[PDB]
């Protein structure tokens, strides 16, 4: 049965709740972003409205094959009526097409659902700046003070440097980047740009990227592997046995791979900075971990919540154990006492 933190009070609306069958009373199913935990359940056979962003809509049509009529894309930053309830979609600064949703209830309550987000100060000068938010449904993925990680711009800097050094040292080396969902496209697009290349990838990955409304995308990507010296592979495949296997296929065209694994947090964030990173090495193949995050650090989350001063907070991540729930509430109480709301 659909959990209460996926339902919006005083509406027929649910959020990211596609895996339970029909939910009784639900006139509308909102989808925050195209990640499989959030969409798990959709198919071609859905005949209830789905409201989502334009970009999420393209992925729904082309990757899952939902029928154009049931996909209601909405533009961002635009006051929109949806069954006589005003709603707004806002950029979540997560993956392509990811949004947060502002719900304006008939009774006067205002609810923000963040979906998955990486909180940022530019959100403090959006339509949120204009009025009070009573209830916050919050992405709590990294709600604990151990979780620090660098800025996205810091990480992209490091990457543009590593890659370009190597390629200029050895002109027969390949850059590989790992992937398993949408998100983090900046890693590979930045590397390719510095190297004067398109990015090469499988047919299915190319299809997915062609749904994202990236400007100039035809100039940036290709399915011709031979012609490219930045390749994307499955994240499963980013290891030595798999990279050897792949290094064979290229047919004596490169004599060294240099790979990047964009990851979330790992325990090596506790004791090692970004300028002081190293790879594992089994012969000519070198694998970097780079902590490029599309979720809020603890500090970024904390600042966003203390600015918003919500009357109530409902976590949507790490809610499956009493210990995590209890740990999170304690942080929420500190934040509230510090900030005086
Ligand atoms: Ni996500």
Image: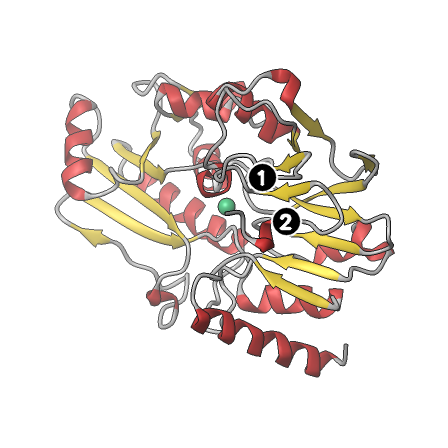
Residue at 44%, 33% (x, y): give it: 192
Image: 258 above or below 323: above
Image: 264 above or below 148: above
Residue 291 spot, x, y in % from top left:
42, 55
Q: Does residue 250 appear in this view?
A: yes
Q: How is the image coloured?
A: secondary structure
- Position of 6 with respect to 279 (left or right) is right
- Position of 238 with respect to 151 (left or right) is left
Nearest to the observer: residue 66 or residue 334: 66
Q: Disc number at residue 7?
A: 2
Mark 1 neighbour density, 10 Å: few (under 14) some (14–19) many (20 or more): some
Place residue 334 in its image quadrant. bottom right
The secondary element bearing badge 2 is classed as loop
> What residue sits right under mark 1 in the picture?
23
Asked if marks 2 and 1 touch (Cβ < 8 Å), the reply is: yes
Nearest to the observer: residue 119 or residue 82: 82
Residue at 65%, 38% (x, y): give it: 26
Residue 64 spot, x, y in % from top left:
47, 23
Mark 2 neighbour density, 10 Å: few (under 14) some (14–19) many (20 or more): some
Nearest to the observer: residue 290 or residue 63: 63
């Amino acid at each position: 049965t659909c959990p209460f933190y996926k339902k919006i009070p005083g509406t027929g609306f649910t959020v990211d709740a596609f895996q339970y069958g029909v939910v009784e009373g639900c006139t509308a199913y909102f989808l925050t972003h195209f990640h499989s935990d959030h969409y798990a359940g959709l198919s071609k056979h859905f005949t209830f409205p789905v409201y989502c962003s334009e970009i999420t809509g393209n992925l729904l049509k082309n990757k899952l094959h939902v029928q154009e009529q049931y996909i209601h894309p909405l533009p961002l930053d635009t006051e929109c009526i949806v069954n006589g309830v005003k709603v707004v979609l806002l950029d979540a600064n997560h993956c392509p097409g990811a949004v947060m949703i502002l719900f304006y209830l008939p009774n006067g309550t205002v609810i923000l659902h963040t979906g998955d987000f990486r909180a940022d100060p530019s959100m403090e000068r959006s339509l949120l700046a204009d009025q009070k938010v009573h209830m916050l449904y919050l992405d709590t993925t990294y709600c604990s003070p151990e979780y620090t990680f660098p800025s996205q711009q810091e990480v992209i800097r490091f990457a543009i440097n590593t890659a370009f050094e190597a390629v200029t040292l050895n002109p027969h080396a390949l850059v590989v980047c790992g992937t398993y969902s949408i998100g983090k496209e900046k890693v590979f697009l930045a590397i390719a740009d510095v190297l004067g290349s398109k990015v090469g990838m499988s047919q299915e990955k190319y299809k997915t990227l062609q749904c994202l409304n990236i400007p100039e995308i035809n100039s940036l990507i290709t399915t011709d592997m031979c012609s490219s010296l930045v390749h994307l592979l499955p994240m499963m495949q980013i290891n030595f046995k798999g990279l050897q296997s792949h290094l064979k296929k290229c047919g004596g065209k490169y004599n060294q791979i240099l790979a990047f694994r964009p990851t979330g947090w790992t325990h090596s964030n506790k004791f090692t900075r970004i300028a002081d990173v190293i790879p594992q090495t089994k012969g000519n193949i070198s694998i970097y971990g780079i902590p490029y995050s599309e979720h809020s650090s603890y500090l970024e989350m904390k600042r966003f919540v203390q600015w918003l001063k919500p009357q109530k907070i409902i976590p949507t991540v790490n809610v499956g154990t009493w210990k995590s729930r209890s740990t999170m509430e304690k942080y929420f109480r500190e934040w509230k006492l510090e900030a005086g709301y």
